[PDB]
Image: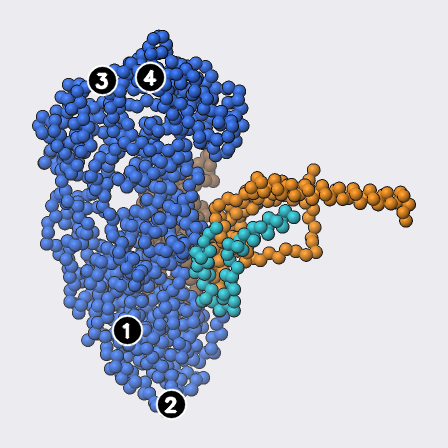
Chain colours: A brown, B blue, C orange, D cyan
Amino acid sequence: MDVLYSLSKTLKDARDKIVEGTLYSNVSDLIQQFNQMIITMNGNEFQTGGIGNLPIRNWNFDFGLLGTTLLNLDANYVETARNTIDYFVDFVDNVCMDEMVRESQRNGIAPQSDSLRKLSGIKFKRINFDNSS
Amino acid sequence: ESILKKLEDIKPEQVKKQTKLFRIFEPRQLPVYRANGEKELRNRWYWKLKRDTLPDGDYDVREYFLNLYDQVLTEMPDYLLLKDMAVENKNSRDAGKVVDSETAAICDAIFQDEETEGVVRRFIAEMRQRVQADRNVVNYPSILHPIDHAFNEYFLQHQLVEPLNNDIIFNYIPERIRNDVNYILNMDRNLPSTARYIRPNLLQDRLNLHDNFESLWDTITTSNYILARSVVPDLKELVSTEAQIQKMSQDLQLEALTIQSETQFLTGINSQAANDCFKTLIAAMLSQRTMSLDFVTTNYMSLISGMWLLTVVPNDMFIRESLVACQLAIINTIIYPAFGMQRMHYRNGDPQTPFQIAEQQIQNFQVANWLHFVNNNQFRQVVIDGVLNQVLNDNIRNGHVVNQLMEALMQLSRQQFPTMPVDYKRSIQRGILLLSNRLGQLVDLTRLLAYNYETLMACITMNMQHVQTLTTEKLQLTSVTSLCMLIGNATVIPSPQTLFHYYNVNVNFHSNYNERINDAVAIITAANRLNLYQKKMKSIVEDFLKRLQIFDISRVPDDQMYRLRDRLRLLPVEIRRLDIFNLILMNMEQIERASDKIAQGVIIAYRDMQLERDEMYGYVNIARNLDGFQQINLEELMRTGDYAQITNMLLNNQPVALVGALPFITDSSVISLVAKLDATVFAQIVKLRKVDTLKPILYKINSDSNDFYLVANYDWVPTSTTKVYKQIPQQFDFRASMHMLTSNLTFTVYSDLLAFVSADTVEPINAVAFDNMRIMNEL
Amino acid sequence: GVLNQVLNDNIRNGHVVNQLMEALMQLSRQQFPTMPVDYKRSIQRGILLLSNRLGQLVDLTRLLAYNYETLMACITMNMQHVQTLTTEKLQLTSVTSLCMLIGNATVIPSPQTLFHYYNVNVNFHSNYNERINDAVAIITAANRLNLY
Amino acid sequence: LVSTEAQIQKMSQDLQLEALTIQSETQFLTGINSQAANDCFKTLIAAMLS
């Protein structure tokens, strides 16, 4: 749950802060966190299940890092970041939906979807950052 | 250079060929005796150790078996053709062949012996080889002890040769060299289906010597740097140094009667320096050796050349202090004076580099953007074709960063220098003009550097680890100025022969590294599993480092060697070595019990026990097992030296079994047995508190004894109070010992695959880069 | 009946050296924020010089503790801990020599060396007590004989 | 004991003292020898015993 929230928070920060013309110093830490997320998620295969009418969806992560070369973010940087962020947002939204539609009588607080259960592994703890909600 | 000689003298791998079957046992004729001890007219064949040299003491026996493991690893071949071992079997009905000549000797001895059964002679007459030429297979009859058969069968079934063909030879070339359109590869031979080759063991570094072995990694990186220097191509058709100096003098407007900074701009401009800079840059990036920047702050041309160098080379390739000094000189000489900013007061040990502070402080977009790029220009760690590589930014590869740098320099030239005398601005402008009159040449040079770097990087087999090294390679900024000022339009790319030589040297070093790792790991694991607690393993690691051929072990302390031992101890053993050691572990007890020099122990009982009947001994006081007897371990007693228990047991006549590899006296005298001498050989233990001198008596009572009539004339079965914990030899069954060893009828093994590939280059004028454009484009 | 100054069990088995290693390994990863980078590198590499000898230092600690215990078994007078007027000056360069040059050759006191040390200690203690007895006897005799 | 030459070279290579600006470049590794190690061993154990 902390890893999923951190993924969503990183994506929201990327959407809000990676904008055309912005100083890189405004996003340096955000870019580092986003690249950490990319590194952690790369090479992992996820599946969001077919409970109810939810389609079964398979997610592969093979993204390259966001650049660190521009003093001010330009349109091309924003477009590449937008592509990556769109894929990640789709994944996170599907994971959230797959988790919301499941319940357990024994351990209802624990993750029920297999994607969130996988994200609860230690290898994803690196993605975790600010929890302010 | 001696380092280059050492690194290029490493041969690929000494290929081992088997000339005879590995044997630990041989048949031997022994006189046999009847149940009453009378000698039979017939003899009998028994399995006996070929070299019975087992030592005294269990620890020494385990040491002997470690040595035997080393011997078997030495004798294990890479491939085997049994027709080489095949010899004529003179008693074969079809005049066939057997392997090895030792088998032929056994067959002749058995066949010629009058005591041999006719069925065995029939069997020897049927022993011949079968050739299946269609499958390229041959089976040969061989006579082997079961352990010998196990070892030889493992050798036969686990050879290292694989089929070789033109496709394999072509794919042996790195994928990036084959994909390059600047090289044309050709072959003039069709390798037959019987061609063979041995793959190099290109496993990546299992010791991670780049992590916490800083001296060893410094040596490795120095060797890599020297080799890279040896293979980096030489610049051709460089601009004439005299003409370039004349042109620079005209551009700088040198004045005889005035002291001017611009004069120093001409310092150290020559073709030797340019070639040295080219080689140093490419070799340092290839070997990932840290570089040190040498420059004089009074030479502003050095600072402009350093601006270019920091633009093209990632800044982690330079030691931090030198990079900081160069950046501070650039900031305080070119940038801040140009923009009228107060001289930067930079603190030694600042977390930020001078360029980062300047980037935060500079309001000019072009200069600040170039500063940001230089700050964030890093290598990219990418696994290409299974090897970790440090890849340059694509803008460096295509040379656009040169355009960004030139934009920054042109912005600097347009500044007013408000607080400086006009001559200072003139000198800075003149240096920038010297650099900017060669903008296209600088783009070409950047592209050439990147292309040569990646082409030679395709030839690296071991992971390129980016870690700052203990020592650095000094790079004079005047050499960078020479390279910038003298580079022409001639494209130089690595020769295909140079690329193949570099790749072969890297492969040889990598394979030797892995093979020596395997040897050391196997030895260490075997010693641990053989419980050799008194063995100091420094010798193993010392031999390992010596065989790597690039370290001076005199300079390596013992602590580092034991750290290497600890790292090696965690690695799994290679499959062939591990299985050979498994065979040795399985069969070492039997091999030891086959020895005639030592016994497995001595049972001191204090009651009459009848001597056992065994055909090859007559009557013998042998114990097959230590059942019903308390055991004293002689190795533990010798290690601890506490003889209280054994002394008390010997003084109290308490039956016991002293267990451990012991030498024994063979005594055939019946009178000696009646006199009970075997029971008189244990008081020295109590007297001297030593057991290394213990030598129990092994009675061998039969008709060859002088006083055997006592046995025969009194219906008397000999008895003794002491027994020797020993095994009797296994009989030699000729039919059971016959095995059909199968191998390939014939093949040819090849060493250097690239010898079959002839490669050439396209015209350098038309050589292209990754972006499909020519590497150099200036007129 | 003899007072003895004994070490923590973690010193005797040499385990605490690991902790030391741990600590200084951390010191090798530290930033040293404002320190010049070359001096920082030298300090961290010296820290690693000591760190990478973890096995040798554990062996040295165990050897030192064992030798101390074995020789302390031969002490017959109470080991009283007092801050003395003068000290034995110990060079930290000698400590560096011991740390960086110790191998794996165990050296323990010889049985004859232990017996000789115990005999010397016993002789000194017995002479001390006997001379105390002689002095006390003579003083008491002089006082009881009224030898003012 | 570990070879004094080998350990001295190792320490010099790791410390890189010559490349520094330390006013005492030679004094850094002085006193690092087998005799000093034996003296330290004896001094420590003897001081603790006495």
Asked if B193 appears above or below B231 in the picture, the reply is above
Instruction: Say which label, 2 or 3, has the lower sequence index.
Output: 3
State which mark lies toward you, 1 or 3.
Answer: 3
Instruction: Say which label, 4 or 2, has the lower sequence index.
Output: 2
Q: Which mark is residue B624?
A: none
Q: Chain of mark 3?
A: B
Q: CA distance from mark 3 to mark 4?
A: 21 Å
Instruction: Say which label, 1 or 3, has the lower sequence index.
Output: 3
Between B191 and B400, the one nearer to me in the picture: B191
Instruction: Say which label, 3 or 4, has the lower sequence index.
Output: 3
> Pointer 4: what residue?
B706
Type of the residue with mark 1: Gln
Instruction: Say which label, 4 or 1, has the lower sequence index.
Output: 1
Same chain for the residues at labels 1 and 3, yes or no?
A: yes
**Is residue B295 found left or right of B32 in the rendered image?**
right
Type of the residue with mark 3: Arg
Q: Residue at x 39, y 55 (%)?
A: B554
**Is residue B582 found left or right of B57 in the rendered image?**
left
**Is residue B703 found left or right of B600 in the rendered image?**
left
> Pointer 1: what residue?
B272
Q: Which percent across, then down, holds residue C113?
A: 58, 42
State which mark lies toward you, 2 or 3.
Answer: 3
Q: CA distance from mark 4 to mark 1?
A: 95 Å
> Pointer 3: what residue?
B42
> Pointer 2: what residue?
B258
